[PDB]
Length: 237
Image (cartoon, rainbow, N blue to C red; front, top):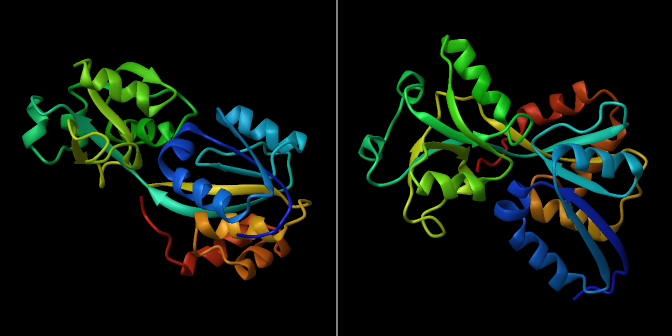
C-alpha cells in the first residue's frame, strides 16, 4: 500500500457511482488507506454546487457543471444509450430498432438534465417524432424496475445494463439513433493536484496520465483542451 495521507472528495452521479466507479474506488482504497475518501453522489446540480463551494475536488459526470467556475474538464469515455425490454416484448427478438419504431412505444427514461437525456430529445426532434415518455426517473435502477414490470421500453445508458446483473433484460443497440455522450472529470483550475489524485484520475481514465492532465491545466480555452483530445481515442462504454 501507499503511505500517502490526505483527503479526496469526489462528487458524481448515480451512473458513475453504480456502473463505472466501484472497482476504481475499491482499488484506490486498497492502495491508499490513509487517504480520506469522501464521495457525494447526487444530481448534476448538487455536483456543480459541491465543486463551486470547494467541497469536492473532482466531479465525474456527463452533464455540465456551473458555467461561472474556472474548471478543467477532461473526457474519460464515450457512451451511448441502449434500448432495453423484457424477453417477451415484441422488440426482444428484433435485435435492432429505428427511431421511427422506437417512437411507437411507451418509453421509460431519464428525466430532463440527467444522464444525457437531451440526446434523446434531440434525436426525436430531428426526426419530427414525439417520444411517448410515460415514466421519467433520475436513475437507471428505477428505470429498470418498471421496464421489468411492463410499463414500457427502457432507454438507458449502456453501462447501466449488462448480461450478468440484468440477465432478464434484452439490450438492443441504439447506435445510429443517438449521438454518443461523453463522461468527463472536472475540477477547479486552482485545485492542488496531489499524487493520489493523479492516480485516481488515471485509474478511472487510463489516457489521463499526469502529463496529459498537467497540460490541460495549463491550456486556458477548453476550446483548446478538446483540440488536444481530437487525436486521442477515448474508450467506449
